[PDB]
Image (cartoon, grey):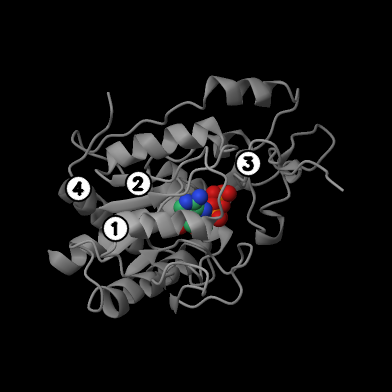
Amino acid sequence: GAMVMRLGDAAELCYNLTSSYLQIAAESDSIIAQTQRAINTTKSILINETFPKWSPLNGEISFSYNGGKDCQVLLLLYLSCLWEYYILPTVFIDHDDTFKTLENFIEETSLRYSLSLYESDRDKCETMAEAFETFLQVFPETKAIVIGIRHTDPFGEHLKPIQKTDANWPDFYRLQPLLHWNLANIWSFLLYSNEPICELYRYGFTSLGNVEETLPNPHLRKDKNSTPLKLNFEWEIENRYKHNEVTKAEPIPIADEDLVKIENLHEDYYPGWYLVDDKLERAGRIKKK
Ligand SMILES: Nc1ncnc2c1ncn2[C@@H]1O[C@H](COP(=O)(O)OP(=O)(O)OP(=O)(O)O)[C@@H](O)[C@H]1O
């Protein structure tokens, strides 16, 4: 059971769930309404500003993919806009310290969505720019790369939806259609989509840095003596997009090695979607000097 979809079927599903999200009846001051607005801006950027300039079909555009929450939301919206526009080269820079659950997830979703995955060499000591230069050598026709970074992410401040790479990178246009999204919008859309998400989030992770530094978020630690946290995504979860027989998905449990690490904490956490404050998204970290 590999939950595999042909690319066209994956695109059509994504178009349907995104359209379905947009049809949710919500109050103007709600998280869902804000998310619908964010989706519209993202669609406009892709359909109106991106696709007419760079062809998503011939290899001009590659999709920067690392299996995280930003990546998956952008992938679902990108697939939606491909279907909308018409009716998948992907690049992951691998590291020696990536969570096994994330590695697994990247592989599983590459299968699920019929992606064409390129991975850099996790055993080569190199910068991201250097890894992308090698990637350019392999795919010299690449003009643009889709990146799901948000303004609230580190180094997210001075970015624009369409922006050339820095001087030390290979020469491409960065396509950054998710900049205006906030953490709450990411969770709301993801939970509603009923698509598989990296299961580390379910255990209290709000970011996925690396195996040595990242911990479940201390703000999400369960304690009899803390005010219990409220869930802002009850509707989305309870009314999540119902899939047909072709498109059915199931979560994939976390890697054995990661469950052992979580169990070793002897502490339980609310899932990551109990966090909606962007300022605390990377709070789950080992104390370093
Ligand atoms: N190692 C990588 N390989 C390919 N793309 C990457 C990589 N790291 C970041 N990116 C790109 O930058 C965007 C930001 O992802 P990042 O993982 O930095 O943010 P996030 O999803 O908010 O955090 P997390 O994954 O820790 O929960 C991603 O959507 C992806 O497009």
Marks 1 and 4: in contact by CB < 8 Å?
A: no
Residue labelled 3 has its Cβ within 8 Å of some atom of ligand 1: no
In the rendered view, would you say 183 is above or below 93? below
The label shown at residue 153 is none
Marks 1 and 3: in contact by CB < 8 Å?
A: no
Residue 240, percent from left and from top: 38, 45
The label shown at residue 118 is 2
Amino acid type, residue under disc 3 in the picture: Asn
Report, in whole angstroms, how far the alpha carbon at label 1 lies from the one at label 2.
10 Å
Report, in whole angstroms, how far the alpha carbon at label 3 lies from the one at label 4.
30 Å
Residue 189, percent from left and from top: 43, 54
Marks 2 and 1: in contact by CB < 8 Å?
A: yes
Nearer mark to the viewer, of 4 and 2:
2
Residue labelled 4 has its Cβ within 8 Å of some atom of ligand 1: no
Nearer mark to the viewer, of 1 and 2:
1
Under tag 3, what secondary structure?
Answer: loop
Amino acid type, residue under disc 2 in the picture: Tyr
* Left or right position of 136 against 213: left
Report, in whole angstroms, how far the alpha carbon at label 4 lies from the one at label 1.
21 Å
Q: Earlier in the sequence, mark 4 or mark 2?
A: 4
Q: Residue at x 37, y 64 (%)?
A: 145
Residue 136 location, quadrant: bottom left
Q: Label 4, on which residue? A: 7
In the rendered view, would you say 200 is above or below 91? above
Q: Nearer the viewer, residue 98 or 273?
A: 98
Q: Earlier in the sequence, mark 2 or mark 3?
A: 2
How crowded is the residue under tag 4: few (<14 C-alpha within 10 Å), some, or many (20+)?
some
* Left or right position of 184 against 191: right
Q: Earlier in the sequence, mark 3 or mark 4?
A: 4
Q: Label 1, on which residue? A: 139
Q: Label 3, on which residue? A: 210
